[PDB]
Image (cartoon, coloured by chain):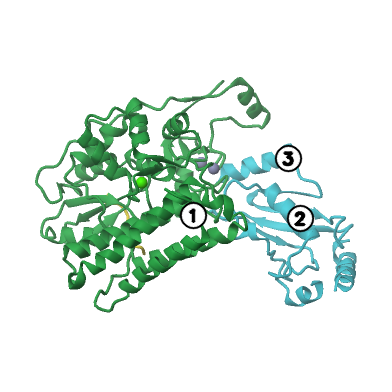
């Protein structure tokens, strides 16, 4: 939980 | 996965490790019996220990589950037969081969690390040689032989 | 520059220490996310400490290392500059919007960059700068032929070199290139900074046309922007889904971080799993996610750099091939799964395997290369030609 998220698909 | 376990059993036959060996039990490629002869460096000398190896469905990305079936006296081995080698846990990496896990256990058999033991009683003792050698030697007489 | 002695080093300590103190002011209320300075500075001190203790009486040859020297003169000029940003900023420091505050924010970043570099060069505390592994084959090849084993070079020396290989159109475009690649803002190019830049701007094949297109002429490119600043800038656009910007990731240097406004009105940021930036942009656009660069209706066409000149297929030498008949297998096959042919190359280590396996190992929480365990800074897709 570092503020980044999985790429949109 | 399945293919990998098949390559491993294959690579194990081509050139195997000394003092040990293994292979599937019945038709199940995910369960192996493995034999480990007592190293001469160690007190278990002259003993024959058998282990089960279970490949989880996650293997090779997760390590195999290895346990001693034959009773042994070690600060790193449970009465459950669970083994405390690190490359079986945090230090596992996918390109490691079963032969290496086996050698590593013989390597562990001749040189146990008490500062991270699985048996608190035998850790204390190990870190008095004369009594620890003596008992390891005897348990091998009852169980290994 | 000039030589580095214990007496100096204790001065940097006091200067860093002041800056810390100037940043603990309760009126400032620095937000705790990276880059966060009260993290950066003490961690830098820590690693500086580890470095020093490793050289014992060998402090002789530590002060005479070109990279270390350039680093201290730069760490010193960067704190002096922050301390002086406080005197001349007065109360404008406590307004989140002020130009002075914006300059502190830019400094936090420079500090993270400096610390990442330091640890890239002195990983365990010992100088590794001479063996440093450039991630990209063709980029590593350029640095070796041009600079050999040097850790650090003057910006002039760097421009001259690169130009012989990758022509720089003008003086302006060179300033733009400088500002982009010099992350520690010291007027040199470390082998570490070189690495970051060529990771960000790959393929090396057309390096500048890549950087021209993703930075120079792209409205979506944000330089020296923080995670939080990316949040703040998209806010104005939160009513307009499809608006995106991208910047360097500061926590993973050499990686891109794309901020975007979702169809539901939230702002997400994503770091493309190793892939080239233009493809994430082109796919993102095509799939409707990245539409309006910095919120503008007009979105650039990146299909120009789309297909680079293909990296040549690997071919097995008879001497290698014959062994795999013996080994009871074939050279091109993934030795992790024994199933798929190797379609992927890990960089820098060089190891080949299949993408399907590399993904599973990464998703499993596994650290680095599955073979050597070294860090994975890159991936180059590849295809093998069997010796047969
Ligand atoms: Ca620089
Ligand atoms: Zn594979
Ligand atoms: Zn590797």
Residue C303: image location, x then y, percent: 22, 33
Chain that is green in the image: C
**Chain B drawn colour:** cyan
**In the image, is the residue at mark 1 within 8 Å of ligand 1 by its beta carbon?**
no
Q: Is residue C258 something one can see in this rendering?
A: yes
**Does the closest atom of ligand 3 sit within 8 Å of the Cβ of label 2?**
no
Name the residue: 43% across, 55% down: C72
**Mark 2, chain letter?**
B
> Between B1 and C187, which is closer to the camera in this rendering?
C187
User: Which mark, residue C4?
Assistant: 1
At mark 3, the secondary structure is: helix
User: Which residue is nearer to you in this view: C304 or C90?
Assistant: C90
Task: Tell me residue C375's x, y (percent).
Answer: 49, 48
Q: How would you rate the neighbour count of disc 3 (Cα within 10 Å): few for under 14, some for 14-19, many for 20 or more?
A: few
Q: Is residue C251 among what the camera can see?
A: no
Q: What is the chain identity of the residue bearing mark 1? A: C
Which residue in the protein does label 2 denote? B107
Colour of chain A in the rendered structure image = yellow
The residue that mark 3 highlights is B13
């Amino acid at each position: 939980s570092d503020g980044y998220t999985p790429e949109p698909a | 996965a399945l293919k990998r376990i098949h390559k491993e059993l294959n690579d194990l036959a081509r050139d195997p490790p000394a003092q040990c060996s293994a292979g599937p039990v019945g038709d199940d490629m995910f369960h192996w019996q493995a034999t480990i002869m007592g190293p001469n460096d160690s007190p278990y000398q002259g003993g024959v220990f058998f282990l089960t190896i279970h490949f989880p469905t996650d293997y090779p990305f997760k390590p195999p589950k290895v346990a001693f079936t034959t009773r042994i006296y070690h600060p790193n081995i449970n009465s459950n037969g669970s083994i405390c080698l690190d490359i079986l846990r945090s230090q596992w990496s996918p390109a490691l081969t079963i032969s290496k896990v086996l050698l590593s256990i013989c390597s562990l058999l001749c040189d146990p690390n008490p500062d991270d033991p699985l048996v608190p009683e035998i850790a204390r003792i190990y870190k008095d040689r004369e009594k620890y050698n003596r008992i390891a030697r005897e348990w091998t007489q009852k169980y290994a032989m | 520059p000039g030589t580095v002695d214990k007496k100096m080093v204790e001065k940097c300590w006091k200067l860093m220490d002041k800056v810390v103190r100037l940043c603990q002011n309760p009126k400032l209320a620095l937000k705790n996310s990276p880059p966060y300075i009260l993290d950066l500075l003490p961690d830098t001190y820590q690693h500086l400490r580890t470095i020093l203790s490793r050289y014992e009486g060998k402090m002789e040859t530590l002060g005479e290392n070109e990279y270390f020297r350039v680093f201290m003169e730069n760490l010193m000029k960067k704190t002096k500059q922050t301390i002086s940003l406080f005197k001349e900023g007065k109360e404008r420091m406590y307004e989140e919007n002020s130009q002075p505050r914006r300059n502190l924010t830019k400094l936090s970043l420079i500090f993270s960059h400096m610390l990442a570099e330091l640890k890239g060069i002195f990983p365990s505390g010992l100088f590794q700068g001479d063996t440093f592994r450039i991630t990209k084959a063709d980029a590593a090849e350029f640095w070796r032929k041009a600079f050999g084993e040097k850790t650090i070079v003057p910006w002039k020396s760097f421009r001259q070199a690169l130009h012989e290989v990758h022509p720089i159109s003008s003086g302006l475009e060179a300033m733009a290139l400088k500002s982009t690649i010099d992350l520690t803002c010291n007027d040199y190019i470390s082998v570490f900074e070189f690495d970051i830049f060529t990771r960000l701007f790959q393929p090396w094949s057309s390096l500048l046309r890549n950087w021209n297109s993703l930075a120079v002429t792209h409205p979506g490119y944000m330089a020296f922007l923080t995670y939080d600043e990316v949040k703040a800038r998209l806010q104005k656009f939160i009513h307009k889904p499809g608006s995106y910007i991208f910047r360097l990731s500061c926590t993973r240097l050499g990686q891109w971080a794309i901020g975007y406004v979702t169809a539901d009105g939230n702002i997400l940021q994503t770091i493309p799993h190793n892939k080239p930036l233009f493809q994430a942009l082109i796919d993102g656009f095509r799939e409707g996610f990245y539409l309006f660069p910095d919120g503008r209706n007009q979105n650039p066409d990146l299909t120009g750099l789309c297909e680079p000149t293909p990296q040549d297929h690997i071919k097995v030498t008879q001497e290698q091939y014959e062994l795999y008949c013996e080994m009871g297998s074939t050279f091109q096959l993934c030795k992790i799964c024994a199933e798929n042919d190797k379609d992927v190359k890990i960089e820098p280590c060089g190891h080949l395997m299949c993408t399907s396996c590399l993904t599973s190992w990464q998703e499993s929480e596994g650290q680095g290369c599955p073979f050597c365990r070294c860090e994975i800074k890159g991936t180059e897709p590849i295809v093998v030609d069997p010796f047969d």
